[PDB]
Image (cartoon, protein in one colour):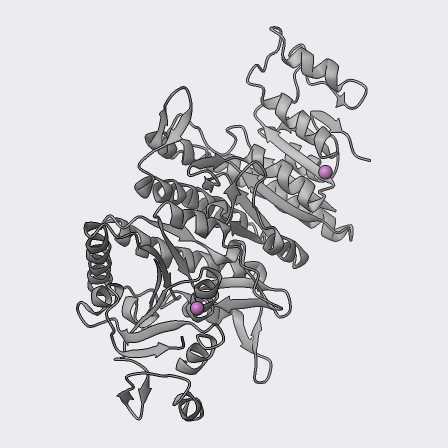
Length: 260
Length: 249
Ligand SMILES: [Hg+2]
Ligand SMILES: [Hg+2]
């Protein structure tokens, strides 16, 4: 039973406030994760868990200084300074999250993409260590990070890039997207379920002018779950117990199911 | 083309003092490395450089808490806490070193083994990222770290493990070992060179062993010199011989 939980939205950090940390939320989230891990142990049910988080007010604020738009394209500059500066900011955010998780006795450990991942048409991302960590009951905590590509450039790898890749690569049984909203909003209300019988209808809706989310973020999550034939929930990570419940397999928000 | 400089734990920290940093040495070292890189580009000569450092006085203090004796071997315990605590200690040391290097405009970046390296039947160490970084003229800084061991569960990979592996894996032209001694000491005296000739007698007399061993198993070529002596590191990066030379072809 492998579950990958993405702590997204702005539940851990306010992107507006530089280097801000939502301490209270982070601690509650840690509490719920611990509560869930304890539940599984008592129910004698095995559970492998991978946590993924973005840069929050740590990554983007730093990366922006090294980002430029040239010929209508994103390009990283002055990276002889920028690669490290971004790595440094992410490392700090990851330290804080892992330290907090460990304070509730969650066996979290650090996975830093910038050290070994290469952004190509097909990511070079060795999961050997991660597999071994999960075998020994550790909880790998992977974060969005700056990474080099295979074309003389760089790229910010995000949680949205990381979750699908690992979901497929490790054959996760469940994907959990903790966000700032209640689910995939159709008429300002989370649609209970998205599957092979309504996905296109939902994606076209999301592409419409009546869509609460026009960022295409939900569309991408849905598309990747279909692609890798996974099952996942998109829910509000800000609501007490949602994370605990989602980790127990209880549908929260919107269920996206394409598992075979 | 590619040189791999190893900074001995002894010259960056004090093993006798947990969480110790030899600030002046570190800064001198960074400065010398900076001057060397400037020398090459001034000659318009392209030089790829990878830096490696051990856990110094950060690993042991913490790792010791998670290392026990089953009878005569090393046993890792409570790694649900220990893996992160050791990672954290190593990350702290690495940050300090890279921040110092960056303060001298050395384009250093962090390579954390714990996140992707696996010990055991054949080292699993993906170098794709490092290769790309070297093409950007970035200076990867790799460090000793706790890593998963598919056989023994856990293992503290050291600079002596990393350097040769990368030396071979990246076809490095020069291997440099900056340490606190004038070279490999035999009867308290630094030997000028170690070849296929005196190697036999040197191996019986004999960490330099485990070190001279793998540099042998990879037909590498390197110099073991004193990193505490002003300008040795600078001179060594310019291809100059310093201390004990081990040119195994
Ligand atoms: Hg899947
Ligand atoms: Hg070699």
